[PDB]
Every structure is written in C-alpha cells, then in structure tokens.
Image (cartoon, coloured by chain):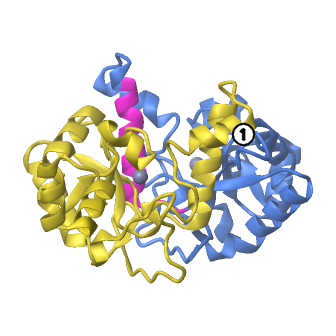
Chain colours: A yellow, B blue
C-alpha cells in the first residue's frame, strides 16, 4: 500500500520511483497525493491560531547529500573527526537514497515564528497530525528503533487510517509495519 | 541591459517580472540565462579544489516571506520589539518584492561541508565570482548604502563586463548604477 512505503537506512528508495510533485506557494514540492491532506492540516492549525510552514518538502538526492554534508561539517567543527562526524550526522540526516523527503511524502514543518513559536507548532502537530494522515515520524521514545534523533518537525504522510492507528498504538512506523507483517 | 536591474525597498520587483526558471540537480532553481555562467563558476571553483553548493537560488514571495518571518522571530526571542526585530531582520533578509532571489539572478553559495569550509568558498568567490559575472552584492563596507549586512554567500548575476568593472572600481551595485547616472 503506497502510503506505507518504508524508507530508512535498511530500506532505500526503489530504483526508478515515480513521483508527481505539486509546488506549494513557498516553492517547496510535495507528492500531489498528499496535497489536500497537508492543506487540511494547515487549515486546521491556523483555525487553532497555530501558524506552520513547510521548511522542507521533496528533496533530490543531491539536496539530501548537501544537508548531510552540512550536518557533517557542523560535527567536525564541534571536535569530531570526519569519521565520527559522519556516524553522528546520520542520527539527524538520512544518507541519500534513504530520506523519506525523496518520496515527496515527508514535510519538515516549522513555526512562521512571528505568530507561533516552534514549540507551539510541534505540540500542535504531535497531538493533531494523525487526523490528517501525518505521523510524527521520529519521536524521542523510538530513536533506538528508527535510528533517528528527536526530529519534532519531520512529519510523514501515511494516510488517516494508518496514522490514527500508529498514534493510538503509540508506535513508530517500523513497529507498526513489523506488527502488520506478523499478523 | 536586463541583467543590471536594481531591486530594493525603493525598487520593488516589477509587476509580472518574467523569470524563466531551470531546476538544478539539488532542486534549486535559477533563471536559465545565468545557467552557463553559474556552471562555469562551479567548474572553475571545483578546478581550484574549492567545493561550493547552491544553498538558495530562486524564491517565491512566500518563501522570502517565511525566511523573513523566521529571522524576525529569532530577534523577538532575543528581546527586540516587533519593530526592532523587523528592522534588524531586514539587514539580513530583503522584504518580499525586493529580493534578487525572486529574480532568479541571485544565489546563496556555501561550502559542500566535507571538501571545503564556508570561508574557503567565501574567499574564493570574493576573488573569482566577477569572472563569471556575479558580484558579492552586499560587501561589509557598503552596508550603509545597500542597507544589508555582510552576507558573503549572496552572489548577484550582473554579467561578466559589468561584474568585472564593479569589482576593479571596488563599488557596490547601488554605487555603479548611480555612476551610470
Ligand atoms: Zn525531515
Ligand atoms: Zn541571498
């Protein structure tokens, strides 16, 4: 099922994955399939006086490389050999060909800052996103399963049916998929 | 000449300005007219063992808006009034309607991280960008004229002849267009 595709270190994007991108007002791009769900989400947040942005939508391989390299540079500057920096940067940034952002199913949502702080948007999304098919992909209690640190901006479209189950079930996507495969 | 357009609070982007955009491999977009020059710039950089990336090309009004609001929020959070936060934010980020990035003639160039540092790239661009017809639009010593802070990553396409002149004359774009008079 298309919305449940697993992309992680162990599950790279399939060769020749087709994606039709819609362009948002801010120039970011998303899978046309998630557009009205994301639109509903933003509509709802604003109706609650919460004002989010799409910081990052679709990213190309090259784009994913540059974010990753910038992340590595940051850790080198904090006293990491480049070998240490790579491994450490990879807990924040997926190596190219393993970011969900390469599907067009992930958005990194932030506050517009002026009407809302990061924390208010992050809270709101955590409690609400599932109603619109989006999950908090990388919660702090599952970093030992996802391989990724607490990333309160990164929301993954999986669809309403699945997001609600995952949210109630209190699980990460890997667990949910693993538990679906078992039964 | 089309490439010398000045753009600021006084000179908002013209109504229906015509951008003719191209996607780069990182997903950033540039006016197609600057494509060969940017490619020549990265080629020469890479040839010099210097490894730049385009962190930002074309931006929508809304994209510009979002950067500016994020900047304003950073200043509000460090105790600036709404009016100060905006004032301060504007020295780093142009207001929508006044950015060169909305022309697709401006690129933010950073280091690729692991082959070069930002300063090495910033240094290189400083000394070589004009050959490809880009200028360091916002030099430190012209913040009074340009109304923008030192932004060593921001390069404006103006053309090789144009960029070369401005660089030797040591001037900022505002200055050169007043030279023309
Ligand atoms: Zn993300
Ligand atoms: Zn810029």
The answer to whether B88 is drawn above or below residue B28 in the figure is above
Q: Position of residue A137 (x, y in %)?
A: 32, 51
Q: Position of residue A15 (x, y in %)?
A: 54, 80
Residue named by callout 1: A83
Which residue lies at the image location 49% right of the left edge and 71% below the top edge?
Answer: A13
Which residue lies at the image location 52% right of the left edge and 48% below the top edge?
Answer: A93
Give the magenta-colored segment's residue range. B58-75
Residue B25 placement, left or right of B126: left
Residue B96 placement, left or right of B156: left
The answer to whether residue A51 shows anywhere in this view is yes
Q: Quadrant of residue A5?
A: bottom left
Residue A146 placement, left or right of B20: left
**Residue toward you, B53 or A11:** A11
Q: Position of residue A105 (x, y in %)?
A: 35, 66
Q: Position of residue B94 (x, y in %)?
A: 48, 45
**Residue toward you, B181 or B15:** B15
The answer to whether B84 is drawn above or below residue B25 in the figure is above
Q: Mark 1 falls on what kind of element?
A: helix
Outermost residue, left side: A47
Q: Quadrant of residue B33?
A: bottom right
Magenta stretch prevailing secondary structure: helix
Q: Was residue A41 drawn as part of the magenta stretch in this picture?
A: no
The answer to whether residue B150 shows anywhere in this view is no
**Residue toward you, A125 or B8:** A125
Which residue lies at the image location 32% right of the left edge and 26% below the top edge?
Answer: B83
| Chain designation of label 1 | A
């Amino acid at each position: 099922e298309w919305s449940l595709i697993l992309v992680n270190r162990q599950n790279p994007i399939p060769a020749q994955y087709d994606v039709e991108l819609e362009q948002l007002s801010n120039g970011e791009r998303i899978d046309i399939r998630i557009s009205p769900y994301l639109q509903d989400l933003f509509d709802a947040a604003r109706a609650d006086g919460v004002y989010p942005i799409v910081a990052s939508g679709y990213r190309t391989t090259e784009k994913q490389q540059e974010i990753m390299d910038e992340k590595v540079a940051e850790y080198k500057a904090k006293g990491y050999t480049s070998a240490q920096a790579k491994a450490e940067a990879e807990t924040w940034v997926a190596v190219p060909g393993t970011s969900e952002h390469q599907l067009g199913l992930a958005v990194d949502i932030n506050a517009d800052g002026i009407h809302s702080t990061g924390n208010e948007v992050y809270r709101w999304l955590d409690e609400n996103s599932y109603r619109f098919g989006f999950i908090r992909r990388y919660p702090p209690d599952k970093t030992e399963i996802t391989g990724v640190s607490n990333e309160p901006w990164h929301y993954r479209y999986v669809g309403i049916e699945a997001a609600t189950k995952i949210y109630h079930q209190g699980l990460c996507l890997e667990e949910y998929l693993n538990t679906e495969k078992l039964e």
